[PDB]
Amino acid sequence: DLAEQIFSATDRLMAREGLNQLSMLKLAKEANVAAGTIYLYFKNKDELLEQFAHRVFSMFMATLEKDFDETKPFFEQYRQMWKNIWYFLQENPTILSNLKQYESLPNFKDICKNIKNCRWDLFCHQAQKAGLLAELSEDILFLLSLKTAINLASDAKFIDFDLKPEILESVIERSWRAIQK
Amino acid sequence: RQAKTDLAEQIFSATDRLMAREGLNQLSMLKLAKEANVAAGTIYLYFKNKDELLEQFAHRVFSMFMATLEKDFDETKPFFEQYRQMWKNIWYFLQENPTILSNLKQYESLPNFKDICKNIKNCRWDLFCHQAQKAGLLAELSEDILFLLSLKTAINLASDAKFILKPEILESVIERSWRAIQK
Ligand SMILES: [Cl-]
């Protein structure tokens, strides 16, 4: 509500000026609220940025869950998560531009590590258990595979893949190919 | 006679450091001269202002990347080994130069990491793709897509090594990222 307004303002301000240039006064300006109002919702910049990081990971998990179907073949589960990332990034240009900056958020590593049993980690376990995937760690598998969606995400490549979906399917299958046992 | 290139590199080296420790936004010429151990006069003579500095720095950054791809290149080896060399070149370069690794993200804000990049005459990657495609080895996908499916892993692994390792694992990634771009 007012919190998402402020988080959304954090993205924009983080995209337009650096993460280093954020202040509670500036964020209040950018969210079109008085300086007092922002402090009603967060005690300080650290807390705001902590909760912001948590909102970012919450979106990431949302994206991995959308139209999840465990009855489908593992490839089609993978294809679905790849497309969810793709289309999420198409729809959210400020988030796309800010992806690299999020790694500098103070709470980012500490939040990232403490997520047990997320949708990707479970997919890798099931898929390894069925004999499909390489016995490599889940991080390395991600980097060889779903990460290609983040790697490729740009405006010119949204246009190209929508015109030639053959290319998008090729990239999905090839990125899957990389993590086959 | 170019002690002028060496002095430029003295300043560029310092640009990296001040960019890695403080932000790119917080750069100013006074701060970069102190870091480089050059007089205020020297840096202002070399570069018209902060803009012209960061332009030339960009070009210098593209050059180091191109030189990294070229190191130990050998047409006579198989295309996989050429690719494996390039992977290792990137991996060990970024591990040896972590200050460069930090600034990778912030580099795209430089004028012009768009313009100066697309405009690269005879890039080793491009050339390699052409020879390997001509031989029949690689997917018929554009050179950037092929990169983003393959060598890109070297950069992503170095970068996320910090936020998340044995030699068999590195070879697995080299071989598997290669696998993604095979015809
Ligand atoms: Cl900054």
Image: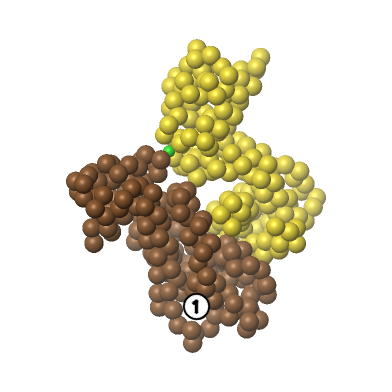
Chain colours: A brown, B yellow
Check disc 1 and give the amino acid type. Gln
Q: Which residue is found at the position 50% from the left and 37% from the top? A: B116
Mark 1 element type: helix
Which residue is at the far front?
A43
Is A62 situated left or right of B102 in this image? left
The quadrant holding residue A93 is: bottom left
Is A170 situated left or right of A155 in this image? right
Provide residue B98's location: percent of width, then percent of height: 61, 42
Provide residue A33's location: percent of width, then percent of height: 20, 48
The residue lying toward the viewer, choosing from A134 and B27, is: B27
Look at the image and tell me in which quarter the N terminus of chain B lies: top right
Q: Which residue is mark 1?
A: A77
Quadrant containing ligand 1 reads top left
The residue lying toward the viewer, choosing from B30 and A116, is: A116
Q: Which residue is found at the position 43% from the left and 68% from the top? A: A61
Provide residue A127's location: percent of width, then percent of height: 59, 79
Above or below A114: residue A106:
above
What chain is tagged by disc 1?
A
Task: Using the rendered image of the protein, determine whether residue A155 is visible from the camera's viewpoint.
Answer: no
Above or below B109: residue A43:
below
Query: In the image, is the residue at mark 1 within 8 Å of ligand 1 by its beta carbon?
Result: no
